[PDB]
Amino acid sequence: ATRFRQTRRRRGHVSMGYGRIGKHRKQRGGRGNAGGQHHRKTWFTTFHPDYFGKHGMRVFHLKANKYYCPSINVDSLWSLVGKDVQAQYKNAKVGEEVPVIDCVKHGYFKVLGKGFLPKQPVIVRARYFSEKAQQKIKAVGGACELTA
Amino acid sequence: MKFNCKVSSNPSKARKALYTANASQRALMMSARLSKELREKYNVIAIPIHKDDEVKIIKGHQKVAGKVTAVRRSKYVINIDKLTKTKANGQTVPIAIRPSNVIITKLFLNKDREALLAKKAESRKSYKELVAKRNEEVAKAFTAVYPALNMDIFGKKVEPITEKKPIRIPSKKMAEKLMSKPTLRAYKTGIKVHKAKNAIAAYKAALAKK
Amino acid sequence: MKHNQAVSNIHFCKDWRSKVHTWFKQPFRKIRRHQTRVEKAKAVFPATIKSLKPSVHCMNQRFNYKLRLGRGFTLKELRAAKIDKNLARTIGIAVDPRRKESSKECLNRNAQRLTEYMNRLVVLPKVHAATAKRLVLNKKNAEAKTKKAAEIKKFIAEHNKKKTKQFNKLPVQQKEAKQVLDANKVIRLTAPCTLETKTLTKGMKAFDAVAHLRKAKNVAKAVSGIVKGQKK
RNA sequence: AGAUUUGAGUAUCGUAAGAGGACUCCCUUAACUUAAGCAUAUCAAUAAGGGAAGGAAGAAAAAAUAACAAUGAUUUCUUAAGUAAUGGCGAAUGAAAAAGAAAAAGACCAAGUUGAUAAGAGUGUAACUAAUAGAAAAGCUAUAUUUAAAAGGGAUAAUUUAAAUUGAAUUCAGAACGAAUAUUGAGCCAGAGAGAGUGAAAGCCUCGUCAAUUUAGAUAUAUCUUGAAAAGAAUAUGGUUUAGAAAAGAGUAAAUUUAUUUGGAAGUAUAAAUCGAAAAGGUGAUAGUAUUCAUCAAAGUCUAAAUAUUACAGGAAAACUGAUAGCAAAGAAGUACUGUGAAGGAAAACUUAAAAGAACUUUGGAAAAAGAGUGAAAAGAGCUUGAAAGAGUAAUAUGUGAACGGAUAAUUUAUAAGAAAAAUAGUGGAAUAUGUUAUAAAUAAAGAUGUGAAAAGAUUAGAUAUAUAAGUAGUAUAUUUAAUAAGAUUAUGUUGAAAUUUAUAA
RNA sequence: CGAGAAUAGAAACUCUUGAAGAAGUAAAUUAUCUACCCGUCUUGAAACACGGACCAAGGAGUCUAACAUGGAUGCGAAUGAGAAUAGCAGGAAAGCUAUAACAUGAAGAGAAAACGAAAAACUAUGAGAGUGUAGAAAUACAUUUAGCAAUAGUAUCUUUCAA
RNA sequence: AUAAACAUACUUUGAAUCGGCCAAGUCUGGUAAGCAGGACUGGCGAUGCGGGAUGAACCGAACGUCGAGAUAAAGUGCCAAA
RNA sequence: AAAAUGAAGACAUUUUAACGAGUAAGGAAACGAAAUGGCGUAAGGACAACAAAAGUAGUAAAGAUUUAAAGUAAUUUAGAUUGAAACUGUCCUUAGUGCAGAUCUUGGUGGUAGUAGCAAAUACUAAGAAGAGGAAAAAAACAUCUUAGAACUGAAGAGGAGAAAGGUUCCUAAACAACAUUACUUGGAUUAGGGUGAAUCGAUCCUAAAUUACAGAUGGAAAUCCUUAAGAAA
RNA sequence: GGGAACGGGCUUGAUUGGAACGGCGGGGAAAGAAGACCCUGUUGAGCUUGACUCUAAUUUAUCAUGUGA
RNA sequence: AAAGACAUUUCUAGUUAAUCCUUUAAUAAUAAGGCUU
RNA sequence: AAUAAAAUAUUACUUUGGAUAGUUUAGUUUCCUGGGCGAUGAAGAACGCAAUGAAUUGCGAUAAGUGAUAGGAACAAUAAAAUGUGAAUAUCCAAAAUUUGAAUGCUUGAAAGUAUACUAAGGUAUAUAUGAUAUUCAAUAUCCA
């Protein structure tokens, strides 16, 4: 909407809100990120202090698929199967059927342990497990299963 | 609506095709309607006009009847021997008439007008009987669903439904608040004007009774 | 630049105006392709099938739990399904000799796909006339096949209570033709998945998943020390 | 003398050239610019120069990715991603696999083998030839599997393209106008109320538009005939008697160096100088050597489809411009005109419905003027309207080295404010108000909890038929027979808020 | 003599002018007071600073792309899926539908290998809700309970040489 | 003691600007300057009005359109109100 | 700013109190007690006589010129004249959206101003003719043609012919709107016709300085070199 | 007089009758030209030079396999 | 020594070997690249 | 002190000028279908042809048009002649198609020209490079009597 721009409220004002002393000239210190080490150094220090330099080792061809590992906390495990299934097997124990939460089927590979688990046995199947994730699962009466 | 992507609904292209039309196409655009007596004789609505025909001017200042003396396809006009103007210095000039302001009252039929009139009459009959085939099929569907009614009802007067069933919807209260100020003022003004018209009518009715 | 902003990285310093591609032909690609699809649906009528494709696993561990349509069945999958590789391309089956047999599970999964397709397949005779040899030979062996099918019915009756054909017969018969556009939409890649439930035992309860992960990691990083020690 | 090789002239039948180059494949080491200077860098496969193509071209069938529960020619789109990486590590530059789609199709040469070898080649045509990747010849055979007389004609049908034909309903009535489509009134058509023309605004005046018809042209579209339905032929795994005891692309792949290029960084690609392989070998992007592993098998060729297009040609649209705008060009526009040349390069739309474009007289040398006349109207051709700047005429007003403006009055001019009506006392109640009744309408319900019906399907177990059938409740389809489990959708109880406010008439 | 308070009373008018033109307003002239050339740069221009003879028409913060803040909106541990693309009716550059790749987010630190968050929290002040009494009109005090947001500080936990 | 709820504390986003000049019961360099440079404050710039005849900065006082009054600086022979 | 009232009244509510200078600059839209309020241009989607003919318009549109009214203002409204066919009001959406300046662009027009000028090339006069075009109180000047007078270039010419360049300007007749700084009956100007005759003059033919081919040589290319050397050519 | 320190305009005075012809060169800091002198731009260009960085031409070394000693 | 479906991890002491991270199919000795100063 | 000639101011009418309004056979952009040239002489250039034409349009010594097939009564500025025994008009057709230009027998400046062969004129063919076939040859290049 060009009728709501500031250009429609500065018609009649000579300089269009750019000043009479310091005009609206072509450049205001260079083009792009020019002068990052000479006259815009105070801007780069203030707002991007680690812009200039090197840090870390180069990876000549990065295989970003190897670092792909979605994670789910223990507190979010039961939401994969829903609260209806969770309440159905609320009084399960050793010996009878216990729901299996296949994280890989839902796109989660590693199970991290954060937050609390409802006090029901559960079988958690995933590729990797955190240390506290296995402790919290076992303390609730469940089991940890490996995949792939 | 037009569903033929080949023809154009652009006014500029329609006028351009009118000015640059060849002589063959200009003949058909210069068409006139047969009179009552000729239409009964041939069952043809209209034909392209021709020299030595007799027409009758039905629109314009002078509704005279005359004989066609020229069919000027460059100007899309015709000339009549009985419609002339004296060009100041004594001599007369024909006055141009559009062929849609006249009706043909007598035909100059040599041999191709006879063939054309026969062809036009036959095509009129075929389309008239084709429409009858469609009309009965549309009538057949109506009867199979409303056996107690006939299709002539669609041409008579219609009796509107008078039942005035209301519905309780929990949005009539909000309606006045769902209008912007410009349309709220118009709606409230119409309510006030409508109410005042009933007030004067009631005053008129009361006086009429007494 | 003034105040707090990101460092701008815009590659417009070249001539982008001649590098601009606009998609004004998008609404008409849909019409052009759909119309070409319909004319493709005729001509090759029936079965404008986009060829039966195998069930293959997506590459890499990021995707390997998913199945997707490959390109062409391997020669072993056709041999296992008892299909001639020369006839396979003519009955709407994709063939790919470039693909190597990856696993037994792949061989069995994609041999079952061909078996299901061959049962759902109806091949019309090469010659429409009723005097064609295949229609003639169908009647000729119809008497003999009745006794041939007698023991096969009881073959699957007692046991279920290498002699295996090199090639199965093509299903060839005269029928009212119904056109399906793609056979990959009839034969699913995988069955729908429901909630899995398992019996909780003390054996699974005591399993130490983290310890096995660390041991697998530590054993992998310990092969370096073995080689250095051996060379010492 | 004769047999060859190589090179010429002539004759015959053909072929290339030039135009165009928007899109396509390439060659060549621009600079302005950015880096707040500048020299690498950037601009940038960019401009200019040069070559070659088609309706598309290019590419295309792994010496390819990957490290997986693995994929699988090429192209194009989405995502990856402004990421990995490159970079006076500054400014800046910058991919690809995986993944999702459109479309899909694989075939040959060389080498090898077969040699009573086949007008033109024996210094070799021709035939066979790959993932069970030691192939290839001739003849018998076993088992599974495929098969109708090919190719070419004729006809019908279907689907499309083009042309032609056809295509409703007021030639309605009144009033008024220079003129009716506008206006008033009564009607009609519509799978047609897109559009144009018509003295002026049209669904029904003309042409058209909707629905259609006919005839031609194609499809590798199906049907029947020619055409018999046989002889045989083909695919694969074997067995056997002879034949045989292979090959797989060289100044290439690499290497040293130089130069350009790349995101490719101890070298991604190209080229040149030198050098130069093979009882094969290439790649896994940190150089080196070793052993494994994985995956391919270069140095010859073709290949539809999905994709691009601001040349040019033919169409259709538009929240685009409306004669200083939109193309430079709404007229004989790349024109007039300029320059030796390469080149440069405009301006200019409108009388009226219809020329009915005054037409005869007087004045004048003529041009013209004044009458007269046409027209609804001079709209009078320098022609729709006709602004401002600048002038002329008429009316009014003022006056000593500026003029104009503002506040306040005076003079003159103009505009401009009205037809009702007294005191007191006899009749006379009329608008309204107070309140009583009756009538009407409106205003209260958001939810909560019960009982059913049920399409489409889904699973399982049976039955019939067809096709196929591995020793894995045989599969698949069509029609039927029962059961479970849910079910989109849908019907209906109970529960739960009134008593007020206006209007109307006495 | 006399405040408060109680008892009772006394105000509804003239004149002049105006459709023969009132009041007001406008225009022109006269008179008193008053008034330097606009735009711009500039400490400062009426400037002996520059542009401006006059009039008409044109004429200058726009479009594409990336990020951020903010006001309105939808949904919300999800949001978008008008990614390509594939279908539908209608003929349609419009509209509707597609258990869906991916983007951003739900987890953060480290150059990287390798990892991956509870003492079901604590402390302070703090929003709100009740009662009683009185002034007395609103309102002002006492007392019971609650402790959100925000800020600051604490234990505990993840990664890092380093929080 | 006094004042202070349209108090106080701010948070985010952003504009313009960083050529300045003047006064003085101030200072430094200079013989000095309507010179150059500073400390504190008030101004002009950005500001018209009443007065100083005239004037960016002096004095009084800061401005919506007006009526009536008391005033400020400063004035009261005429121009010019007294 | 605070109280009060609040489904629609209306003037963007009622009351009370304080306040109002301003360059650069800021205050997008929407927000019932509104987190500023509005005017104008053009186009798009709607709405515009509620009872079945539903904004205005040949009983006069837009535009133009003025006269009055409303508004603080941007502007709006109406009358009259002119003009004759389209247009307007409200809400949203959209922008090629508001000019006094840019030595701004294009076009048109003033003062200067009836002014500076129409002063090199010695020079014209008389009678007659033609023509609308020497009249007149000397309006002292008058273009073309003939005759007479008086003169100039002075034969290295203001003479008679050619080359290049121009291109019909050549000749004749009719005609004078424009053009030749007055005028023109004149013209190299307007209109229409007519006109250029070669065996012997030239071109054509020959070669000069030089120039360009096939084949060849060279170059990434375009193309360059070679002209008788390189050739089964000439 | 003050003012941007040399007014046609402003303040106070001197003074003024409207329209102009021929001259004239005091003024209009008169017209012509975005000062060419001077300075500033992180603006150029011609020319010079062991200014920095390069390059044609020239030069030197190696490689590019004729036979018999 | 204690838990573990018809294998394999944990705790304890002795031993031997390797040991800051990377060069992305796995290792090795050179080489190079990271981190802190 | 005085006059209003010039000057100034407002309105009406007229004029110079061409703004404004209304309008559009012209543009711009997007999309769809093709992308169909040439030694059988292309694109481009020149010249010529209408009863009265200068441009433009169309055409090529058969000239603003010929035949055939459709088509059915006009054209016009003026006059002719023709015309239902077929006027306009349309075309992927047939005939014809000047000089050039890749330009190709040789030459070409603005150049007029000119050779040979086949069939006096007129008309054809004859550039360069190149493939296939035929024919005539050349070189002791290899054998070879």
Image (spheres, coloured by chain):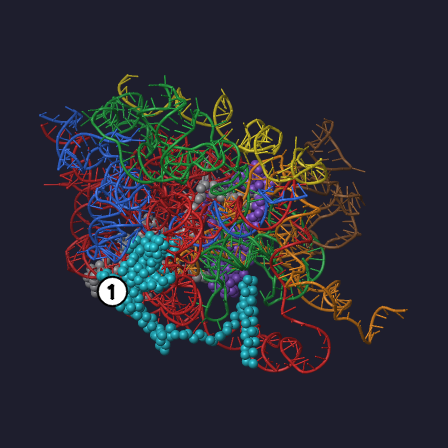
Chain colours: A purple, B cyan, D red, E orange, F brown, G green, H yellow, J blue
Q: Amino acid at mark 1?
A: Ala
Residue H40 drawn above or below residue J6: above
Residue for point 35% across, 74% down: B151
Residue for point 26% across, 66% down: B122
**Which secondary structure lies at badge 1?**
helix
- The number of numbered badges drawn on the structure is 1
Question: On the picture, is D448 further left or further right than D174?
Answer: right
Q: In this view of the protein, can residue A102 be seen by the observer?
A: yes
Residue G228 drawn above or below residue E113: above
Q: Position of residue B47 (x, y in %)?
A: 29, 62
Question: Which quadrant would residue E48 be assigned to in this image?
Answer: top right
D405 or A144, which is in the foreground?
A: D405
Q: Position of residue G150 (x, y in %)?
A: 41, 23
Q: In this view of the protein, can residue A125 be seen by the observer?
A: no
Q: Position of residue D476 (x, y in %)?
A: 32, 63
Question: Which quadrant would residue D155 be assigned to in this image?
Answer: bottom left
Residue neighbourhood size for the residue with mark 1, other residues' Cα within 10 Å, grouped as few (<14), some (14–19), many (≥20):
some
Residue B7 drawn above or below residue G179: below
- From the image, tell me which residue sits under label 1: B118
Q: Position of residue G112 (x, y in %)?
A: 54, 36
A104 or C49, which is in the foreground?
A: C49
Residue for point 28% across, 67% down: B38
Residue for point 35% across, 53% down: B89
Question: Which quadrant would residue E146 be assigned to in this image?
Answer: bottom right
Q: Chain of mark 1?
A: B
Question: On the picture, is D460 further left or further right than F11?
Answer: left
D348 or D395, which is in the foreground?
A: D395
Residue G43 drawn above or below residue D482: above
